[PDB]
Length: 6
Image (cartoon, rainbow, N blue to C red; front, side, top):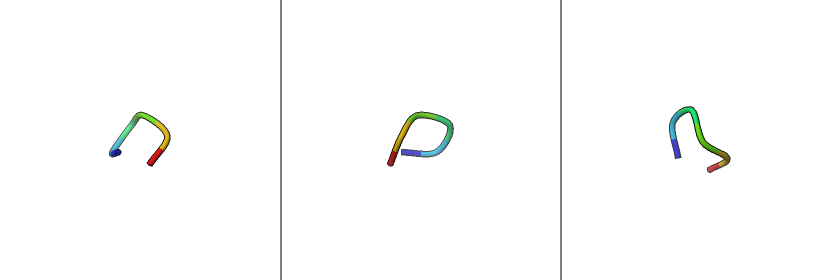
């Protein structure tokens, strides 16, 4: 998710 994993 963007700048957090997926």
